[PDB]
């Protein structure tokens, strides 16, 4: 009795009781799996379509056709032939989109203003009904794919990824190159024949079948309405009845086992990768054997494996468990980072891994553990934070291929059966004869034979001698490896306290004293048994010079290091904390189930105020920290540009250079002395937010104070004597440039900042609307036409109460060229604005309003927003409504004037600075015309530079 | 054979061999004693006339007629009848003048541009040949005299002065009121008859006689030329053959002896004054018995009297020796400040004084001591720094009454005969039966019977019981009081090192390293065996908050406190040091004979780096420091205005309030810990200047470094990471006012700052020429016509690289009135400038040039100038020539424009701030017309105030 397009309906979708959203499952006649989500309060709607095809179905001759294809798909359709029609519609209706290819999945998704779902879906749908696939872009698009590849070329992580693929069976599709590039996309085709337009079309026509598609749609409309909408748009997708691809033989045969790889990294890291091929455990999701083992093998603290490897001073971090492969196969991995001593004991490290394993075989599957995991995940599922719509549908579309409708939400969180047998089964694969091991370290440089062909990775491939393998099999049992004990942090009070009648819509200041300032809000919307605790400890000794910055950093690193064992239980129990230094002191945050928060907070604070430094932990943390500062050189060029702009524009900021130099003056005695000093006098500013009462907030706040006062003898640092840092003020019509060499990448980085004025409602909305207007053109113009790089960003920059427009580009071209192109873009944008219809303008106003008003979905999102107002000392909690009201009154002329005053080449108040991060070797047409530009004043000393310019005031508190 | 006007010539004037100046003594026929000084290199000339009449010859009915008289004398003459002709001539020719009355002397002096000596002297001379004495000023002048009196009314020092006079014989002129006021000057005359115009004339005509006058004149002209000039101008002064006044009976008879006075102070101090009347020792200057005793009784360190009084924790400072009275009598005094414990032991304190005395009688005069004093003073005289001309002639004119021509220079420095007899003679007066004692302390408040009539001082007068007197006579001998030992610091190497051929005209940077920056110049002009050593130690821990400011202060106070005994010898030996904290760290300066500098510097630095705090010294220094912060409330209203402006305009500055509050958190352990921290990391910037070689400078600099590094383990604070403070930047057209209560004075204070722009050659000379032009009008208008107060100041203000115009007034009127009057003055000045002749303008340019170019006369003057360039990090050593060159190119129009841009009510870039320090009770006509003014923005929080305004850059180094 269902509509002819629908085979089967619903299933009753099993969801969390807390979840007010309404759900319905569907199976279209044409084989499409579908989940509809009705949320009547949602500000943005969203949809995702996932194709169960990826780079694994890439033809042998054209690797990356899959990736290439989704690039081409966005590029206009028969009904909507404009090349950027999709994205421009999304931009102009508060929307955004993205897409991705993995081995077996291609996932396309977007969100949009809830009032225009139908129109966003009609367009998205066309991509699966009639793509133009025209060759005017086929040639450009390749550039974007190429630089995409290029950017990741020097990225270690990606290099290792594609290196585990070539270290495997070449006649297995796993070995194929997923990303693609210009070398195998435009080029190999002409010089070997073959039309990459015809090839695309074939692929798209063999593999783009409805039987292999899943869709998820979220909107305000009712389920019935969404049903019709979906049926109408998607029911006529073409079914090709493609058998689902499968890879059951497994990419790593006995020949690839017992292998060892010495890889040379770009960054100066030391990592060890251990890998056991395993059969596909997908079908077993109701019991999850691979992650019961992952849970014990990647466990931390008391008696765990990592604990031991840490005590030998061999390893700092351990991650272990099951890893995706493709339908038919998986892997079980165990990764660790090596200390200096660790790198000399790889063999002995691994022996310990098999020793813990062996201990598992000895001990055998344990029901109480699985039972514990079961109960945590259940609560975790019930009390899951409400997700952002765009990320939810995308995740759901993917999961639709693996589970029945009624179980698409609960799958992967809820366990059921306990299965000792399945667990033993996987356990049996973890043996020396199944092991692939990979060491990454710069100590191999110059002495590698092989070049992985796509990324260029140096590396050695060798076989692990029999005796070694034999030693590992001779893995007996190390007494130390104990199992985890019952989890004390598992919460049992999920009572949601009633809303105090004195409650308020924004955080209220409930305590203003010389020692502490406490902001507090009781949750009035999410009603989950969760609380966010935020503390900012102020002390001048944290950032007073580079030596104390270093000491502040090491202190917390050392503190966290020794709390870890104890803290892991909490984390598994959905209770986490963060602790880091800042230019003002230290930041302590605790999030999660509120029930046992007070016990964790007590332990952290106690340890803070009574800490005692293990000599040995000290040198390791320091050597790591040391190596980490050096490692900054390896970062992306754009990441460097941003780092230097931040230093440049701040009255006081210590560069990594300065920190490195000062690090060698840090000894154990010095550090021991510095702690009491740091803790000697303090001011604390706090936000406590969530499922807590006023009484409970003050109580939590007292215990922090009292624990410090009694144990470290802390006394009050009056707020009035806390020195805050100002932003540097650029001179009218000035242009400064700071130029630096990057010594790894053959790409250059660039950040251009046009500083405007002190933050305020009007200045804020001028900058933000102007940015909205240019957000998609910047993308469509500088990236999708001019192909200047994979990274092309524009938008607002905020810091120290000041703001301005920034552009960020990573590119093969020289900075001065990017620079000229950006100015060229600025002119076009100005004309574009002069020549834009009023109603297009209003859509831009309306689009920015929607983004701004879009309410946080979860506590930590609402919390972070408020914490932003505290950090910045503006305390403007009602900001969003105010600014949007003001936004709605702007007119084209206002934005034009704004532009002419602040941003034009000829602006009387242009304030421009550029950071140019030069490539390794570098350096020092129909296109629109760039204006002539001034000669930059060149910065050779950030300090001299700042000393010679005035400083901004600080922003007045709201 | 001498000119008929000259009785006797010269004497051959005994002078220092080092002294290139030429001298000649004279005795005019009319009894005038005269010294001429020819200095052909002098930039400014000078003269002084001293009359041997003072407030002691004041008629009984009109006290202060003497003071009054010299006010009236400046007020125009028959030949030069313009009321301010004298001072306006001096202003317009790089000159300045002043005058003063004491008991037996009235001293008038001026300096002037060397090119216009004759014209300045002609006018000065008229005052002693034919004063108009007109009654149009007689009525105004009284105001200035009155506020003069009023200002000192709340000044403790003056109150005690006039209180020792009324505690004496009323029929002795000593008891008369010296200052005068409106109460006894305009008033008592009408209501008791008597013309204060006729009275003046009488006085002036009985006492203003040539026989009682001495003159001293310094100019470029030759001695012969000065002779004629003087004879011509002064030979016809009228001789009245007044017998020289004398007061031989003595103001304090046996009735006033054995007295005790409990005085209530304005400031919260504790002081004890012990006073022995003695006969006049003037005649005995060749042997100076009073100051051989002063030398031993006011000695400090090893075995001295003060040492003991300090160990009992009774007293911090001791000053002892002979004190001026008047021809016929003197006093020998011994003053100390009391700790809290001291005030409870006055009796026991004094007993110790007589015990030391008794020890002197026991021991008897010692030839070696007098011999030591003799030799020090001789070297001191030979190597005396060349004096500023204005202060030299004034001093010499005074000394001309007491010594023969040929000995006027050497008198009071050179000893001759040793006279055990004279010493014993004075020693015999120091006995309990001769003693007057005075205690000053707020602990007496409310319980005094008597009001000294002129100042209003509360106080009790009582007689010292017999037994007390008896106890003091029963002053035996305290073992501890040892004599001073031979003086090891007495220098013996006065060799002037040859001028290295690599020498330079300005300090050169000879050492730029992470630990130290060393500026060095070898003396190329004074050639005295003297050196100035200046060290600025930078550490952020000195001023990081109020607690560390306090600790930095106490540290140095404690350090100096324990070095004193050791240092006194040096000081007597012409070798001194200064040591104080700053917002950047600490300042150590050492000046004097270079020979033993290195031994003193070594001891100071050593002690700095190894200091150990006596518990007991600690509480005393702290209680004193504490009391001292409270005592700021007692300061002059104008002094408060200046203090608050400095806080207001500096990015970071800790108020005395903040320091007081933070002081109670300072304990001994805390302080002990803070020292190593402070010394932990340091940067040093030095100026070494004088009679030292490059090799000797570096050597001196190394020993400071090496002594710190080896003993406190100091390591380098890189200069680049030293945070310097900026000046606050006022907004265009802004007017801010900070208003505060003064709780002691019935006068209000005011400072008005019109901030201009960052310092630079042009901005500097605009402000400085404008100031020159208005310097005398401001005086003549706001003070001498409008009589707004005794304190009326205007001129340049420099701080943190910024500058502006300031006016400072202390007044009976309310701030808003002064404020209006000042603006009224500004308008007049503008018109005055528009309407001033070109050649009058040029004289102003020429007058400022002369002041600026006028070369330093001594090492520490040249040193201080250079140290100014270092402190301020501008290093503009050739400043003076540059700025004057630029000065000479300015025109009226430039100054007008300057004024219209920056200073007018209507200036588009006026930047005005006013500090108003209100009187105790207060508050919150032909006159020129004040313009309407804006409503001030009012400051209630210096901090909020600064946070809301931008900050200036720092000035670029030259």
Image (tube, coloured by chain):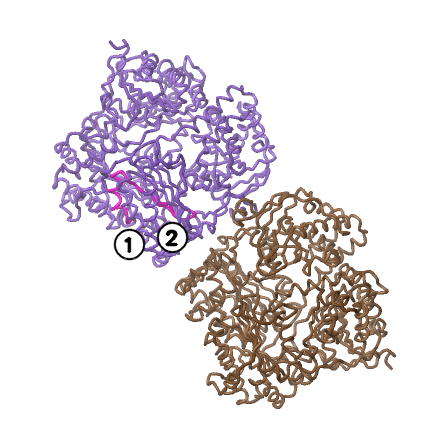
Chain colours: A brown, B purple
Chain holding disc 2: B
| Discs 2 and 1 share one subunit | yes
Residue on which disc 1 sits = B616
Image quarter of residue B833: top right
Please give the name of the residue rendered at 23% of the width and 47% of the height, measured from the top-left corner.
Answer: B307
Residue B569 on the magenta segment? yes
| Percent of width and height locating residue A122 | 83, 67
Judge by depth and name the residue closer to the eye, B938 or A245: A245
Residue B377, given in percent of the width and then of the height, sits at 23, 33
In the image, A113: left or right of B172? right
| Mark 2 crowd level (few <14, some 14–19, many ≥20, 10 Å Cα) | many
Q: Say which chain tag 1 marks.
A: B
Q: Rounded to the nearest whole Å, what is the CA distance between mark 2 and mark 1?
A: 16 Å
Placement of A54 over or under B348, stated as above or below: below
- Of the 4 image quadrants, the one containing the N terminus of chain B is top left
Task: Specify whether A143 is left or right of B486.
Answer: right
Answer whether residue B146 is magenta in the image.
no
SS at circle 1 = helix
Quarter of the image where one finds residue A365: bottom right
The residue at which mark 2 appears reads as B551
First of labels 2, 1 by sequence position: 2
Label 1 CA crowd tier, 10 Å (few <14, some 14–19, many 20+): few
Residue extent of the magenta highlight: B561-588
> Quick check: B377 left or right of A556?
left
Q: Is residue B446 visible?
A: no
Residue A123 is marked as none
Residue A88 position in % (x across, y down)? 78, 59
Q: Nearer the viewer, mark 2 or mark 1?
A: 2
Considering depth in this image, is B21 or A501 the residue closer to the camera? B21
């Amino acid at each position: 009795m269902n509509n002819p397009a629908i085979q089967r309906i619903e299933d009753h979708i099993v969801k969390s009781p807390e979840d007010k959203r309404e759900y319905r499952g569907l199976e279209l006649a044409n084989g499409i799996k579908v989940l509809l989500i009705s949320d009547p309060t949602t500000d943005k709607s969203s949809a995702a379509l996932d194709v169960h095809i990826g780079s694994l179905s890439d033809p042998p001759n054209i690797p990356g056709l899959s990736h290439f294809c989704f690039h081409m798909l966005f590029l206009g359709t028969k009904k909507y032939p404009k090349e950027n029609e999709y994205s421009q519609f999304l931009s102009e209706h508060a929307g955004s989109s993205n897409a991705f290819t993995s081995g077996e999945h291609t996932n396309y998704y977007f969100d949009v203003s809830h009032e225009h779902l139908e129109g966003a879906l009609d367009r998205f749908a066309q991509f699966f009904l009639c793509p133009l696939f025209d060759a005017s872009c086929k040639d450009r698009e390749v550039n974007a794919v190429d630089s995409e590849h290029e950017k990741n070329v020097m990225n270690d992580a990606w290099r290792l990824f594609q290196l585990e693929k070539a270290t495997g069976n070449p006649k297995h599709p796993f070995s194929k190159f997923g990303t693609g590039n210009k070398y195998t996309l435009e080029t190999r085709p002409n010089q070997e024949g073959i039309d990459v337009r015809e090839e695309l079309l074939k692929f798209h026509s063999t593999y783009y079948s409805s039987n292999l598609m899943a869709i998820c749609v979220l909107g305000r409309e009712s389920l019935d309405d969404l049903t019709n909408l979906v049926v109408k748009l998607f029911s006529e997708v073409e079914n090709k009845n493609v058998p689902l691809p499968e890879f059951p033989e497994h990419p790593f045969q006995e020949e690839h086992l017992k292998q060892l790889y010495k890889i040379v990294p770009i960054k100066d890291i030391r990592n060890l990768y251990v890998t056991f091929p395993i059969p596909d455990l997908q079908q077993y999701y109701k019991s999850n054997p691979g992650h019961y083992l992952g849970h014990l093998i990647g466990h931390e603290g008391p008696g765990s494996l990592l604990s031991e490897l840490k005590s030998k001073g061999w390893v700092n971090t351990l991650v272990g468990g099951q890893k995706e492969g493709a339908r038919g196969f998986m892997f079980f991995i165990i990764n660790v980072d090596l200390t200096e001593e660790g790198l000399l004991h790889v063999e002995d490290i691994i022996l310990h891994m098999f020793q813990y394993i062996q201990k598992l075989r000895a001990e055998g599957p344990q029901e109480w553990v699985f039972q514990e995991c079961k109960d945590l995940n259940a609560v975790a599922f019930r009390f899951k934070d409400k997700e952002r719509p765009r990320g939810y549908t995308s995740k759901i579309a993917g999961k639709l291929h693996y589970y029945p409708l009624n179980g698409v939400l609960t799958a992967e969180y809820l366990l059921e059966e306990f299965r000792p047998d399945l667990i033993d089964m996987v356990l049996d694969k973890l043996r020396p004869e199944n092991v692939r091991v990979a060491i990454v370290s710069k100590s191999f440089e110059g002495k590698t034979d092989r070049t992985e062909q796509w990324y260029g990775t140096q590396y050695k491939q060798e076989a692990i001698p029999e005796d070694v393998i034999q030693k590992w099999q001779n893995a007996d049992l190390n007494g130390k490896f104990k199992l985890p004990t019952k989890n004390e942090f598992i919460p049992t009070n999920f009572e949601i306290l009633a809303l105090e009648k004195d409650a308020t819509p924004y955080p209220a200041l409930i305590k203003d004293t010389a020692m502490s300032k406490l902001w507090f809000k009781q949750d009035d919307k999410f009603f989950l048994p969760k609380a966010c605790l935020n503390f900012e400890f102020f002390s001048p000794f944290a950032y007073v010079d580079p030596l104390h910055c270093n000491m502040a950093y090491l202190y917390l690193e050392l503190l966290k290091d020794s709390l870890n064992e104890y803290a892991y239980a909490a984390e598994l129990a959905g209770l986490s904390y963060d602790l880091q230094n800042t230019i003002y002191g230290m930041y302590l945050s605790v999030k999660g189930y509120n029930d046992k928060q007070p016990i964790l907070l007590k332990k952290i604070t106690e340890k803070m105020a009574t800490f005692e430094i293990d000599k040995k932990r000290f040198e390791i943390i320091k050597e790591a920290y040391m190596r980490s500062l050096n490692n900054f050189r390896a970062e992306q060029p754009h990441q460097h540009a941003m780092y230097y702009l931040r230093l440049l524009m701040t009255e006081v900021a210590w560069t990594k250079d300065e920190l490195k130099e000062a690090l060698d003056d840090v000894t154990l005695p010095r550090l021991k002395a510095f702690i009491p000093q740091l803790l000697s006098r303090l001011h604390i500013e706090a936000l406590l937010h969530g499922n807590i009462t006023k009484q409970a907030a003050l109580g939590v706040m007292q215990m922090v104070e009292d624990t410090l006062i009694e144990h470290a003898h802390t006394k009050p640092l009056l707020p009035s004597q806390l020195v805050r840092y100002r932003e540097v003020q650029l001179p009218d019509r000035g242009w400064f440039v700071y130029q630096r060499r990057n010594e790894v990448h053959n790409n250059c980085g660039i950040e251009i900042y046009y500083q405007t004025d002190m933050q305020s409602t009007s200045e804020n909305m001028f900058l933000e609307l102007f940015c909205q207007i240019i957000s998609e053109p910047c993308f469509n113009t500088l990236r999708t036409k001019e192909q200047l790089g994979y990274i092309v960003f524009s938008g607002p920059r905020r810091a120290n109460g000041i703001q301005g427009l920034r552009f960020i580009i990573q590119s093969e071209k020289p900075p001065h060229y990017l620079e000229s192109r950006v100015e060229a873009f600025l002119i076009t944008m100005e004309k574009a604005i002069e020549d834009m219809t009023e109603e297009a303008f209003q859509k831009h106003i309306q689009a920015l309003a929607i983004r701004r008003l879009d309410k946080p979905k979860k506590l930590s999102a609402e919390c972070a927003k408020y914490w932003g107002e505290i950090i910045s000392q503006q305390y403007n909690y009602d900001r969003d409504n105010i600014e949007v009201a003001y936004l709605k009154t702007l007119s084209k002329d206002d934005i034009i004037k704004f532009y002419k005053e602040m941003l034009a080449v000829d602006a009387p108040r242009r304030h421009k600075v550029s950071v140019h991060v030069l490539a390794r070797e570098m350096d020092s047409i129909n296109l629109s015309e760039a204006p002539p530009l001034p000669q930059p004043e060149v910065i050779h000393n950030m300090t001299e530079f700042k000393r010679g310019l005035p400083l901004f005031p600080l922003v007045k508190p709201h």
